[PDB]
Length: 51
DNA sequence: CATCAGTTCGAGTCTGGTACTGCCCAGTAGTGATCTTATTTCATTATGGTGA
Image (cartoon, rainbow, N blue to C red; front, top):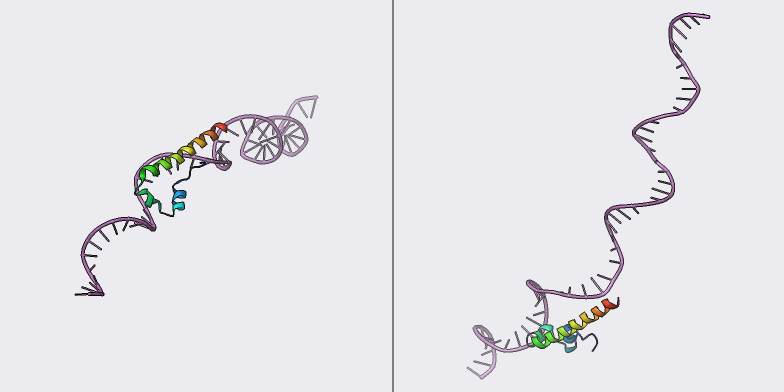
């Protein structure tokens, strides 16, 4: 979806500290972080072009 | 026997080590205008002694 959420939003929704997820599932968490960062970078790029 | 002391497992919490975003201000050098001042001219003004 839009602004794929970040680590903070996912952790707040799950009610767990970020280290709790981070100590067991690094690959998928890095996948979510990369997706969010890529969406932000793409949106910034379109904003730069349009501006 | 059931109490207390020595051991484990995993979660809570901080923090370093590593990368990254969305946004206008501040200083400097041009001009043109308008004063501003240490310094350079344009007249009067007083002092002077002697041959007609």
